[PDB]
Amino acid sequence: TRKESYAIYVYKVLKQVHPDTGISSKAMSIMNSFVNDVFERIAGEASRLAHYNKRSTITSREIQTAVRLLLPGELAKHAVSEGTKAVTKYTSA
Amino acid sequence: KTRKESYAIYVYKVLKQVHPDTGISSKAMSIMNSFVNDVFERIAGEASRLAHYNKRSTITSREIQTAVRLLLPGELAKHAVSEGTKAVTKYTSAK
Amino acid sequence: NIQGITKPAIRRLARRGGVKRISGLIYEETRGVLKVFLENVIRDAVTYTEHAKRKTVTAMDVVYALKRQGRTLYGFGG
Amino acid sequence: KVLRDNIQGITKPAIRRLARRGGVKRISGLIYEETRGVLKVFLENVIRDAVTYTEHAKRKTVTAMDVVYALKRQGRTLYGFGG
Amino acid sequence: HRYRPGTVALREIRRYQKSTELLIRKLPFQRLVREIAQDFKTDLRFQSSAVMALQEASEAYLVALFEDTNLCAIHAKRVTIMPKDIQLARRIRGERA
Amino acid sequence: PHRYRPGTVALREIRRYQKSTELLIRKLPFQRLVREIAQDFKTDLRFQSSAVMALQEASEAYLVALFEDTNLCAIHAKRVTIMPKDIQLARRIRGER
Amino acid sequence: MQIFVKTLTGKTITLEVEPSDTIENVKAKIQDKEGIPPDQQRLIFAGKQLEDGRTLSDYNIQKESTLHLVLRL
Amino acid sequence: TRSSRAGLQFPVGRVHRLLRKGNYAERVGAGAPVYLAAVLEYLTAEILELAGNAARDNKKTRIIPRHLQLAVRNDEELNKLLGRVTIAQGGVLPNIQSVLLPK
Amino acid sequence: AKTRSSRAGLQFPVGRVHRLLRKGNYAERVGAGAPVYLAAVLEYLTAEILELAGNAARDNKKTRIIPRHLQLAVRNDEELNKLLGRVTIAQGGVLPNIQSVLLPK
DNA sequence: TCGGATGTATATATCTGACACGTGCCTGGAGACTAGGGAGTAATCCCCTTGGCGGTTAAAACGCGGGGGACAGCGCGTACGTGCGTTTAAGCGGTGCTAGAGCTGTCTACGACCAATTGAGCGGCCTCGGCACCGGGATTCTCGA
DNA sequence: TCGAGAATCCCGGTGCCGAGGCCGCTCAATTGGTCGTAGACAGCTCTAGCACCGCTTAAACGCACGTACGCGCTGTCCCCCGCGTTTTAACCGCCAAGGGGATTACTCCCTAGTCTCCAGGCACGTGTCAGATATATACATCCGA
């Protein structure tokens, strides 16, 4: 049956960054595993913190603090800047 | 006046059952509270992860048995398994 | 301020481990190591209490920050 | 069917090559035997986990994905085989 | 009289291994903690129990590190600890890069 | 009859083996060892090829890391050749049993 | 009559002597057969120290005795 | 009740409620809490028995955290289980390396 | 448009992340801004990794990325080594380093 | 200190199988609407933190004599690196086969929700003897002999 | 060895506060019942894991030979260690002030849930050119002079 993956999106990001480069299947599996692991870590930590503060729902602030706790400084602030930019762009329209 | 629940009474009951004439300090009681909570959280998390990994939405006694067999070393694992199955059989025998 | 960790205190701490003949600049080395460790744990606790929307650091924040680093501590309600 | 005397299958030159990957220059006479023990213990852990997973799935074939789970439990996550 | 070097050290080792109390004075540690936390946020208040927990954690970590340092020092056929032993132990532990 | 000085071919092999990426241990002996080990826990088990491949990769990585730490300890101990005591010291410091 | 002497290295020395053998004489014997200069030796028999002008029998030293020496430096 | 039906000391209803409210699964079985309570009771009984014996050795009638630390560190399986946790006011096992001792 | 991903101008799917978060049993009720934030973070990290890997492959005059390039890119960046200190990747290899005094005089 | 020899980086043809791309179709995602419960907001209490003063005494700081430890130079003999011929089992490659993994239908017992009820567990009070502190003597090492 | 000087453990008396117990109360666990579906069971098909045999050759094994390194011995120089005197600030006890952590009541609007529609992404299929293989050459480097 169907087997979900992260193919088209990673390929699109690669095309956006480097216009004339290609990658093999093993690198594809490695990137898929890396994305899944990062997703699992961030989501688990955010949910844990949300129940830690006795709150019954998860919101953008929880993920912001999870990113601040997980990633070290410089790329953490880069990622939070990207996230805020995306959030305001989405809510504007 | 918040109703903060704990495990003090049950630990005291177990201690009196095992050792008749012995007392316990408050710090030891807090230590036991923390230890029991940590072990409970570990076992429950591992069992839930395994149940979700086998794409089943119901957590039963078998998942708990497998999690116990995973986390604890050999001798304690076998003793805990024996105690658990004995308790389950005793509970299901009556009604 | 960091000087406040007195040399005889470091000597006692090492004597608990069981060292016999202390020598050199292990005092300065220990001070640096302690500073780094405190910096990390304090940053984690401060982030926790920042999200909590409070102004007083509590024991739960420190216990939980220690829990994150795989250094669980027993005996403070955590 | 019973199997025996497989530990000796890890030949000495292969161990020398593995050491040479890590950056070693000289090798003592007595190290090899010692190493042949340590590796064994490693395997004796991870397989013990993997089989248990196959016990819970009610199967008879050990799957690589179970090995990935077992390696993940010990905090040595591995990438390249899914999950 | 006079004692030969190496006996009072052993007596202190036994005495401190037998006991269970802290060895760093409370006030300088509290001042250091407040000064360190001053940088990350201004006008912060600390409960006493948090400082106590931090003190205990620091003591345990330092004791373990000194244990490993002693092991390395006796390994190279010496008796005195020097900083290179601390660096080696920290590097093998996987803490330092 | 030319004869290279000791340590030259060793360095050349060092560079060669750090340059490449393929695995080192052969296939059939490793497969037989894995089957023999798994026989004890439960009889009549069948293995997938990718499982054996992953086990081999993990084992090689772990062994290489251990050898690197052993070399670090040996060079600290003012020697050039590694000895088993260095291996057990590295294992002890890592926190393994 | 023969005596055994115990050193700090765990080696026992067997020496033939007589009760008239003064401490000068026995110390000379140790120096001759072992090469140790006389000024480096202290002797204890039955827990007592001795003065060089005396003789062996003054400390009730019998045969087969065990006398301990200490090196002083 | 339900603890009486199984001859347990730890509560069963509390464990059931914690499992249900702990967002572990959509539904829970009727046998899991009994098993978990039995395991917890066994572990705490072992720890308490060891700690009480250690306190008996020192000729005291009340358990203080040092007794718990000694009981945990002396056993080897229990030490393996609690490998990465520190106990407040615990202490250190009294060992000394062989070389350091005087000749 | 219609898709939520185009609304935020992102490439990673928003609806898929929302569904995974809802069905992953993390909280009883999930917010509405969380998927956008998470997708942005994932996109940034993937872009960084891919750019570093592409540069590493460029240095070796090969137009295709193999796992060795990913290993070199990850291990040559200090922070990225920090984030993945307990992760191994197949066929990666090791960094070419040699101790000082080991070298011939 | 050179010079012969050897391993290595580079230039070049080439053929293949893995990678990039077009197609059809199926299911999960988007649009419009409801409703109700969780979260933000305002006001009040009183509890724990901050701040400071006095004193006392224990610990900290400083200086000195010396001996035991760290480190460098030297000799040795033994264990390991390198080369070569012989022996051996890993690896490639086609063939048979079936046990066992994976998907499909069924129906059934097991668990979620809900109304009524009552007693098990928690907050508050009080009481005492096991443990902390102090004074005293027997015991056991430890340095100079 | 050994004997005297301290350091330490064992013994006995005294006082005080934390633990063990008792009492009163409130909300969560029990009981009885209905209704829906997660999964156990039985069956069917199709793949890949096991066993097999033959041929090739690259890899492993055993043996000589030589020399560089681990190890023990020795000598020197100096850096902490034990001890006594002067200096200081930690801690205990006490008192004042007040900020904000914790509750309680009220209001609103944000997300789960419903249905209907349709287009994004999946397996399938196919063509082709980037890299591995094999070959040939010039450059860098190493050990005897």
Image (cartoon, coloured by chain):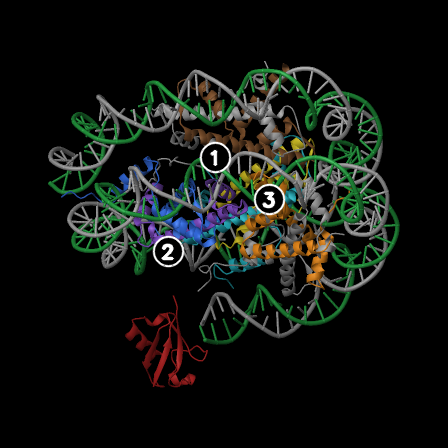
Chain colours: A brown, B orange, C yellow, D purple, E cyan, F blue, G red, K green
Q: Position of residue G15 (x, y in %)?
A: 32, 80
Residue beneath disc 1: D82
Q: Nearer the viewer, residue B19 or D8?
A: D8
Chain holding disc 1: D
* Residue D39 visible in the shown view: no
Disc 1 is placed on an element classified as loop
Question: Are marks 3 and 1 in one subunit?
Answer: no
Q: Position of residue B87 (x, y in %)?
A: 66, 55
Q: Which residue is mark 3?
A: B47
Q: Crowding near pointer 3: few (<14 within 10 Å), some, many (20+)?
A: many
Chain on which label 2 sits: D
Please tell me how crowded label 1 is: few (under 14), some (14-19), or many (20+) other residues with Cα within 10 Å. some
- On screen, residue K95 versus residue G71, left or right, reads right
- What is the distance, in whole Å, between disc 1 and disc 2 at their CAs? 33 Å
In the drawing, what numbered circle is on residue D4? 2
At numbered mark 2, what does the secondary structure look like: helix, strand or loop? loop
SS at circle 3: helix
In space, the residues marked 2 and 3 are separated at their CA atoms by 36 Å
Badge 1 amino acid: Gly
Q: Quadrant of residue G23?
A: bottom left
